[PDB]
Image (cartoon, helix red, strand yellow):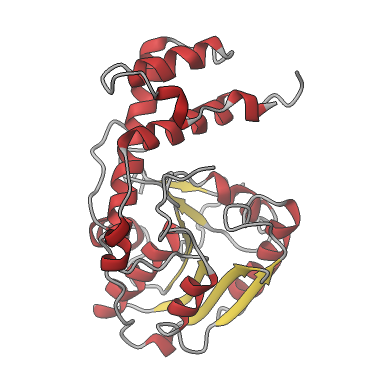
Length: 300
C-alpha cells in the first residue's frame, strides 16, 4: 500500500518479500512517529511494527478534524494491506486515544484486536476540560517552530534551551507577521533553509497541532465492545510545551480514569521523569521496548 502516505515503515524491514502487517503505532500530538524510532530499534530483530502520521504531516494534504475521523481513515490504511488478520495497536499520549478509538471501531465491525498498548493517553472530560479551555494559535506556532528548530539542528557540538522560542517573544508581533518572525529567526539561528520553505512547514504543522489538539478536546471516551477480547496494556511513569491544556496533561487521575474502560489491563511503570519524558529518557524507552517485546511475543 504505497498510496497510504501517513504510514511509514518503522524497522529495517524494507527487504522482506512478505512481512507481518499487524503491529501499528499511532502518532502523538505532533503527528510524527519519531518518538517510536528507538522502540522500533530494540525490536527490529524479532517483530515488525509500523508507524502512522497525521494526514497532511509529510504531504500537502488537509488535516482531519475529529478523533473518530482520523481513526476511520487509518483503519483503511490498516485494512488495505492486511485484509482480515487481527491487529496490534499502540499509541503515546494522543496516539493512545486514537488506537483506543480504533479498537472501538474495529470491534464494532467483525474485526478483532489482539493487543492494545496505551502509553499514557490523556483522558478528556469535555465539560471540565472545556470549562477552563485556554488554547491559542500562537502557542501552536511556538510548538511547531521549536519542533522544527530541534529537528533541523541535531548537532550537539557548539545549548538548545537558548535556541528555543518562548511565548513572550511574540508579545508585540501581529498574528499575520508571526509565522514570518518565527521563520526569520530560525534562519538567524543556523537553520540555513529558504525562508518560504520554513514559513510553509511551520504553519503546515501548526495547522495539524491545532487540529490534533482540538480533536482531543472533543473526544468522548466510550466503552470498548468486548474489551476482554484484547490484551490490554497501560504504560505509565513512576508514582514548557503548554500547547496541551492543563486538563490534557497526563496525570495519575487520567490513568485511573482509563482503567475503568480497560478491565484486566496490565499497568507497566517506568522511572521516566515526566509524561513528556516517557519516550525520551534512554532507560524508559528500554523498559518500554523490553515490555513491548513480551506483548508482541504473546501473539497466539
